Amino acid sequence: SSFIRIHKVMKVLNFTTKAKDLHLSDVFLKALNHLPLEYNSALYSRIFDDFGTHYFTSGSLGGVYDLLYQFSSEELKNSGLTEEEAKHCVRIETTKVEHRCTTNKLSEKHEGSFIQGAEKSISLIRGGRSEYGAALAWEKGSSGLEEKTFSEWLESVKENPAVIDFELAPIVDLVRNIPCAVT
Amino acid sequence: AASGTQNNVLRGEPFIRGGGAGFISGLSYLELDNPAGNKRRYSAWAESVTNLPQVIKQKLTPLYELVKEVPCASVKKLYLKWALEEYLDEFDPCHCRPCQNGGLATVEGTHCLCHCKPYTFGAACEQGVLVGNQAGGVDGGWSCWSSWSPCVQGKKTRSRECNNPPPSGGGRSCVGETTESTQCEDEELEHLR
Amino acid sequence: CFCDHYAWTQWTSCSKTCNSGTQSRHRQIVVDKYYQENFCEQICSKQETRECNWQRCPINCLLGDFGPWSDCDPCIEKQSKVRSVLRPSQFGGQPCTAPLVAFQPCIPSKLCKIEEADCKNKFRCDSGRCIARKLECNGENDCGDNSDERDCGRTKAVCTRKYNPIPSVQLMGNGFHFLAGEPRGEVLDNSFT
Amino acid sequence: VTLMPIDCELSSWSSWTTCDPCQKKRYRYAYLLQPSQFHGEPCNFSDKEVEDCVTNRPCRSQVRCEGFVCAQTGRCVNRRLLCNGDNDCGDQSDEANCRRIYKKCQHEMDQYWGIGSLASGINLFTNSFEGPVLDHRYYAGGCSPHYILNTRFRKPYNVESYTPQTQGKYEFILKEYESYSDFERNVTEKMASKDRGKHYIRRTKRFSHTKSVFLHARSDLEVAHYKLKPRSLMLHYEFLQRVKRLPLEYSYGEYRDLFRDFGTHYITEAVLGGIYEYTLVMNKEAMERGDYTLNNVHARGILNEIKDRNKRDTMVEDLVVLVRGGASEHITTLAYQELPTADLMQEWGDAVQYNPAIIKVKVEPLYELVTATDFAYSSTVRQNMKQALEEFQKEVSSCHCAPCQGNGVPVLKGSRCDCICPVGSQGLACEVSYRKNTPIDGKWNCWSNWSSCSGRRKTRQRQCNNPPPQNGGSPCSGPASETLDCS
Amino acid sequence: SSPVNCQWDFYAPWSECNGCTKTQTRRRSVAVYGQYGGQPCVGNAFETQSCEPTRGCPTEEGCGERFRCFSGQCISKSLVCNGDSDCDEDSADEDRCEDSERRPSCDIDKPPPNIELTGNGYNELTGQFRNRVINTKSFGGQCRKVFSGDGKDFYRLSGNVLSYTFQVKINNDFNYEFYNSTWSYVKHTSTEHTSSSRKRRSSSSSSRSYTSHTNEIHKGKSYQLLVVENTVEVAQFINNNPEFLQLAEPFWKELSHLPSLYDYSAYRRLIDQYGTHYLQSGSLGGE
Ligand SMILES: *[C@@H]1O[C@H](CO)[C@@H](O)[C@H](O)[C@@H]1O
Ligand SMILES: *[C@H]1O[C@H](CO)[C@@H](O)[C@H](O)[C@@H]1O
Ligand SMILES: *[C@H]1O[C@H](CO)[C@@H](O)[C@H](O)[C@@H]1O
Ligand SMILES: *[C@@H]1O[C@@H](C)[C@@H](O)[C@@H](O)[C@@H]1O
Ligand SMILES: [Ca+2]
């Protein structure tokens, strides 16, 4: 049995958002203008279902690779040979004479084999571009990293990252310069 | 006297969604020497899916929530809501006496079809053999909801019997609450009129 | 030993319907000159055992009954009704299925106190966004509406070459939903120059 | 050949209708009592007759047009569609005398690949396409761009969506069986005494070997999904005009000849792509007998010796391949007897995108197009067309054909029936084959007419081809008797 | 199990009378659903007849200060001659405008590669996608560009959509399991005799062989493979809430023609075309 797990986290990019005077998304600014001036729990809750609760003040834009590979193999082997023999002779006389003999014999042979195997792999990729990410995710993983496939995927990640880690401020700090903003 | 036999059965069912039609027909074509599929063809498919994707995971909002900007919109919204509940009650698989061998069922309008799991077949899924990991037994199927109780103390109630089939031979029980209760319809009648 | 000389018995039904049971199968061993001589006692396995029903027991959703209809919003002409999750669903239990918030039309009972932008020296885009006056006739669409460029003379000097934006830059401007652990909607405009 | 060629018989004529208020005509027709088959006479002698009349009744046939009436086609285009730089009348009449042209389409645009095929009606009872019923060359305002890959397309007005849903099943089975048996039984016997003697031998074999292969490969490729608008469809000129020729009074003939030209239903939603199917069946046998003997006797003496040896072998193999959608070289190279290389499969699926077949359909019956915005007396045309559709389904269903031999499928092509043969038989009845038996599938006779009321009954007998003959296959899959309420 | 032939129930009481069509409809439930290959219910789950309505047919309401598109939908007068087809279906907002009054609304005219599939309906019970419910391409007079990077191309988003993103995720799962078994057996048996005698002269002798032998060979092989592989290429589309969504023209037209009373035969024909739900969010990719 053999097992191999790989996890790699790569950070091709790393950004910080301003502290003040940010320019807001059109669809967000529309929903903030639409909200009632008096409190309603349902209508204001719907902002969190649509836009979430916090925004990234800094983070790492990255690619992630995860692989598990797991192999089991079993063999059984059998061989056997056998022989058995018995022989029985007699003479009687008194003119009259008789002489006799008899035999019984056996052999057996056996062979047997049983081979059994299981292989599993599980892999996740985040970030990159689907042709190279496919090429890397498709690796059964029996030897761990194939550095050619991995380095083509990492060159994809530089062109199309995914989020890996982050720092947060609440969405409510952004709601600035709309009508009735403070309210 | 001497005798021998062989049987060999080889099956495979590649299924693909998304990607370009040529890449799909190339990748789904089964190499018996490499039945998982080839690195090159599969990577080409993964390129093409960037340009011909399909929705593969989704979160759902009920269709009545879109009734807007028409005459009678407020009333049409509630009647589409009740028609969804009536459609769900017409097509909910509880109307089907369930299939053997782990098969789900669907309502084909007036009719029940079994979706037999791999290499098991026939109308009840009685024929053939299963493949892969199994828990064994017969898992518990619901019978349909009993008809809704008439707004006693301002709320309806209904009950479901878990007896179609009853969980048997060690199979897992029916999933969901055995009973439900809800507010009445006076809000539609009074407020919208 | 050819341990396959004794049967592929059916696995006995899983001990638990959920939260990691186990199931086992035992060989139909008859001890004989074959079993004795071929080392069967030493190196066969007499019964196999494995995990089954590893999935945690399914937890169904329970919703509360709805609250009162809320104080009606004079600028929206609707009133809102809410209910609370008693326990969320998880581990494959039935989803809450019905809506968790509801709306009804209303005859309001107050005026609207909302105010116009009137935004000093700044430039009011057609969408009402008061962008910086430096961006009027700048030659890039800074209102999103193009309204900063509706009619202009010789526009100010845009950055000379075409340049692409940073890879995935709009992910830096999506909002994140901390309780669900995921991005939800574009909150910052990371196409703005 | 066991055949008798059977001639077509149409009925005696209907009585005439009384003269139509708006067509100024009268009509009579015949029912096909027996289709022509097995090279009987070609028949089709005019199934309908029509005459003129003097008219003593009023007519209101002019459904007005707030639009513009197109000069040649009579179509009512909405007045905003004039001078858009496009042919909305069908025969260009909307773009005459325009002081300027106001193009909406800023760019060049394709029609979606094959979108015009779906504009024609289907004879659902034979799955045959028929004449054009909808105008997918009409766009109204149009000119909102859609992209499949990098190509830009202009959506027809009648089409609600054409979109590249893109899916592929492949299914493979290779089932193989081998079975062999060998038997041998030798004997030897001797005697001598000092005179007399004997010697004798027998030696023998019986043997058999048998093999079977069943192989089946299917690719169901989908490349687009299509749905038609549910309402306000712009109909095709040739259909719009034959519907305006229909009598107000019910003559079956003039409604039947609409269905024989434009089909019975229209495609409201469809799944587009290609089928590749390949299926091989092989059976192989080898058989032997050997028998050898000597007898020798002495006292004067005699000898006899015999040898008998026999070998037999057979193989029988059938292959069927079926391809739908694509381009002619990919079609033929897949049509070829040897399973594809993946390169051809790739090129076939790539070509299926540009010429799809229809995999699955949602129909509506064609009278649902006959809306009062296009036709006067529309409700009486609808009710006639509904009744004709029931009577016609009872004519064009292939249950009328005499039974094929050799498990042939009879198809009623026109007033004439063709037995489409399976692989391994030939001749017009599928009679000419080397085979000792082949499974007959059961064939239904036509379903007997509605009897009485308070719940009517219809009956079927599986008699047209009885299921069991020559080691028969499956008895027919449908309801052997059926019932429906007056009210 | 036996085939079960389908059976209808008795007809239900009628629904209130439809003003616009001057009719009443009544329902008929399936009493026994057909099962195990038994015959389906022939005829219809409904019937409809003429009636004199108390309740009248409702009217449209007008677009007022908004621009009326030919469908009956209303759009803002800022979108007339925007240079985009801002009315769904057949634009009318673009009609007979001057070449100096038309302007480029945006640099580019190309949406993300299957954004139309994100505005489809969904049927929860059949699991199938259903026809167009949301207009996914209402550009709202805005040039909302995204650079992608999974394909190296700019695309234009609708003004409605909350977010659309091209971060990839690829998840692969492989399971392969095989066994091969072989047995071989041989047996041989032999039995023999001889005897000789003399008595006085007279004498006799005899001998024998008997033998039996047997072989068996047996094999079983099994292999199973499962692969489940998923790709996401637009790892999120997040559609807006119903207030800011723009409906598809033929969906809004069918909604307009809903009878304003509980005739389930009308609402079932919407649900059969457009499904039970709409997609609030999801991932585009492949499987
Ligand atoms: C229709 O049919 C009869 C048949 O005798 C004709 O003679 C006559 O013209 C009638 O109108
Ligand atoms: C109870 O629940 C569903 C909807 O929640 C119904 O559609 C089903 O038929 C059952 O009665
Ligand atoms: C029942 O349907 C109509 C009713 O007259 C006819 O085609 C015929 O009676 C059929 O059996
Ligand atoms: C199996 O299923 C649940 C629902 C209960 O019946 C327990 O027996 C166990 O978790
Ligand atoms: Ca024109």
Image (cartoon, grey):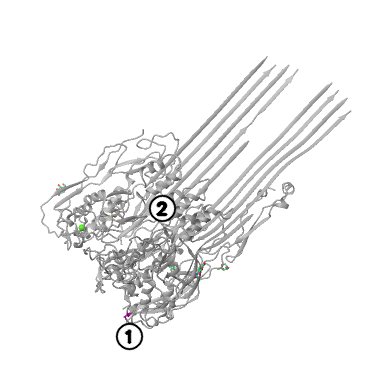
Q: In this orientation, which residue lies closer to the viewer: D280 or D470?
A: D280
Q: Residues within 10 Å of mark 2 (few under 14, many from 20)?
A: many
Q: Which residue is denoted by mark 1 in the rendering?
A: C110
Q: Are marks 2 and 1 on the same chain?
A: no
Furthest residue in direction right, as rendered: A94
Dividing the picture into quadrants, the one containing residue A69 is bottom right
Asked whether the beta carbons under mark 2 and mark 1 sit within 8 Å of each other, the answer is no
Q: x, y percentage for residue D456? A: 33, 57
- Asked which secondary structure carries label 2, the reply is loop
Residue D69 shows which numbered tag? none
Is E179 situated left or right of D116 in this image? Answer: right
> Please, which chain is the residue tagged with disc 1 on?
C
Q: Is residue E149 magenta?
A: no
Q: x, y percentage for residue D119? A: 28, 53
E86 is higher (above) or lower (below) than E180? below
Hey, what amino acid is under mark 1? Lys
Q: In this orientation, which residue lies closer to the viewer: E131 or B103?
A: E131
Q: x, y percentage for residue A100? A: 82, 30
Hey, what amino acid is under mark 2? Gly
> Please, which chain is the residue tagged with disc 2 on?
B
Label tally: 2
Q: Residues within 10 Å of mark 1 (few under 14, many from 20)?
A: few
Is A117 situated left or right of E97 in this image? Answer: right
From the viewer's perspective, is the residue at label 2 or at label 1 nearer? 2
Q: Which residue is denoted by mark 2 in the rendering?
A: B20
Is E60 situated left or right of B8 in this image? Answer: left
- Could you give the CA–CA distance between mark 2 and mark 1, rounded to whole angstroms? 57 Å
Q: Which SS type dominates the magenta stretch?
A: loop
- Asked which secondary structure carries label 1, the reply is loop
Please give the range of residues in magenta.
Answer: C116-120
Q: Is residue D186 visible?
A: yes
Residue plotted at (29% across, 37% down): D40
